Amino acid sequence: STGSATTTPIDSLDDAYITPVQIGTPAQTLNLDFDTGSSDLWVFSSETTASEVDGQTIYTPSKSTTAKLLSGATWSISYGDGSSSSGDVYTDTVSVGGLTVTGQAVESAKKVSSSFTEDSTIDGLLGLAFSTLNTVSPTQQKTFFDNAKASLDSPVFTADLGYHAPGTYNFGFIDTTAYTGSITYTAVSTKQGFWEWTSTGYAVGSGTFKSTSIDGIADTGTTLLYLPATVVSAYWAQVSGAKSSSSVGGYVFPCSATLPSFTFGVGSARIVIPGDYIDFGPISTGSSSCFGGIQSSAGIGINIFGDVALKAAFVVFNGATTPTLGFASK
């Protein structure tokens, strides 16, 4: 069987993408952020501290006939941006675009951090990374992709994110109309629990391709593209008036400038990110300094191919025994 759900940018900058997910019987639809950089299905539930909730839809397991408390289980997660959440774990029927998984761990948030509270449009996260990163103790739990994998026509899910437009998440099938040319597949390392791959190089605007290995993670839960300082500096050196502001916390550019594109290698193939995708608008309302879409990964310790890089491609996440990533033009 398959599943097809539409994903939509939360705001005018594509800061995140929410995808509708049905939890329980009768179903309750929550808008979850599909994150291929984490493996937890957590939601804002009726058990959250009423102070940490600001206009979000809440999962009410007491109003669900198929909800079972996963007795004793707890989860504690901290993200790359510094955000965090914790609580107890429930099991319930979860569906994504028609694809149903019965007995899926739905982590009820009892406590959420301030970044989550501010995001009223995001009701929780749907972890699509390897289940080895799941934070449920004492019994580690599997992701929705893992639980659905056996009943899927093909053990894959695809991400087709849009630039200032809605896109799609498909499960169990490859939509041959959603891309042009071929899908280039590349090896994935499951060691750190992420979809870890090696980019074959890069180019800045119409510059000559630089063939160099760049290990990274295909991460839908991260907004920007985070590459090594050497690669990012080469990119921002081609933008007039661009600098790395320590007060902003990253690279800024004059809003009047037209950004060049950024090409990243996938095997012998190339994925071109239009310069427009790299423009995150003014740093503050009315400002003349604009936030860059390419930032350095120096502090993170991992290079991240986030939404900036992924929305320029049709991306296949192959969860076969030998997992691989596929990138195609669109």
Image (cartoon, helix red, strand yellow):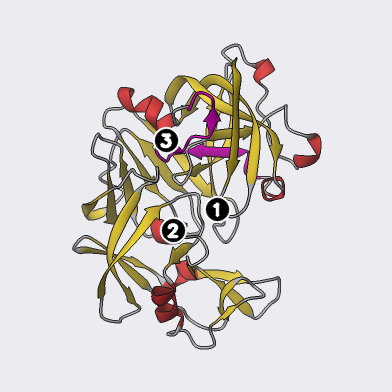
**Residue in the image at 18% along x and 63% along y:** 268
Spatial distance from mark 1 to mark 3, Cα to Cα?
A: 17 Å
Is residue 181 visible in the rendered image? The answer is: yes
The location of residue 203, given as percent across then percent down, is: 31, 75
Task: Let me know if residue 139 is in the magenta part.
Answer: yes
The location of residue 63, given as percent across then percent down, is: 67, 16
Spatial distance from mark 2 to mark 3, Cα to Cα?
A: 18 Å
Horizontal side, residue 46 vs residue 92: left or right: right
**Marks 1,2: beta carbons within 8 A:** yes
Mark closer to the chain start, 1 or 2: 1
Residue picked out by circle 1: 80
The relative height of residue 15 versus residue 6 in the rendered view (above or below) is below
Horizontal side, residue 6 vs residue 287: left or right: left
Mark closer to the chain start, 1 or 3: 1
**Marks 1,3: beta carbons within 8 A:** no
Task: Let me know if residue 97 is in the magenta part.
Answer: no
**Which residues make up the magenta segment?**
121-140
Residue picked out by circle 3: 132
Q: Amino acid at mark 3?
A: Thr
Q: Amino acid at mark 2?
A: Ile
Residue picked out by circle 2: 302
Q: Residues within 10 Å of mark 1 (few under 14, many from 20)?
A: few
What is the count of numbered marks? 3
Q: Secondary structure at mark 3?
A: helix
Q: Amino acid at mark 1?
A: Gly
